[PDB]
Structures are given as structure tokens and as C-alpha cells.
Image (tube, rainbow over all chains, first blue to last red; front, side):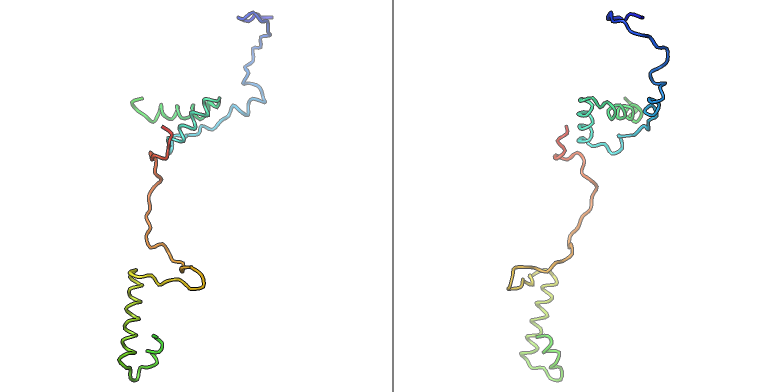
Length: 72
Length: 69
């Protein structure tokens, strides 16, 4: 068994975690664009949700900002 | 009043014509909005009417009700 950096032994698997058949469904995603009609309440709600561990709407919003804004 | 004036078309008296003129003047005042027709005496209730004044605008972003910034 391969020893982890923390010192806890484990088993090494060469196959990716995303290659599992059950995980294949969640791999395909539709990239929504929440930057259409932005509202300060909407942005605040997205940030609040990302604080608790959502991390999805914030990621899509950041992707939209990095392409819509030329200076950024 | 106006029906009685309509009936007395062959020869109208001075008072009947004066009353009809006063009635039509009151009706024009009501139409122009310068006076209220009133409400029925049995219970306080005014007749329903359409919106005389109406404006349209897009939703107000950046208003002080946002409280998000």
C-alpha cells in the first residue's frame, strides 16, 4: 500500500474518479449565464450562497465577468 | 329632469329649460372631473372606473430598496 503524505496508508487506483459510470451523469453540465440582468440583490444572494458552500453560481458569474468585461 | 324636458318639446317653459340647462351643465362638470357624482345614500360606495392616469417603466434597479450594496 502507498503511504500518504500525512502518514495514513491507502490504496492507489490509476483510473480517474470522474471516469465512473455513476459520475458520468453529473460531468455533463449546461453552463448557465447569470450575468444577464444582474441585480445587486441577486449578486448578494449569489455571494451569500457561495459563502455556505454553493460555489456554482459564483463560478458561472466569474466566468461571465472574465469574458464580458474587456478591462478585467 | 332631462326626460321631462324631452317630453315637453312642443313648447318648453322658462323654468323647464333652465332646469335642463343646469342639469347638462352639471353633467359636463362631472365629465370634466370638476365635481363628484356622489355615492348612494344606503351605503358609501362609488362606482368603479378605469385608470385615468397610467405610466409605464422598466424595473428600477439600483433603487434604495435594493439593500444589497
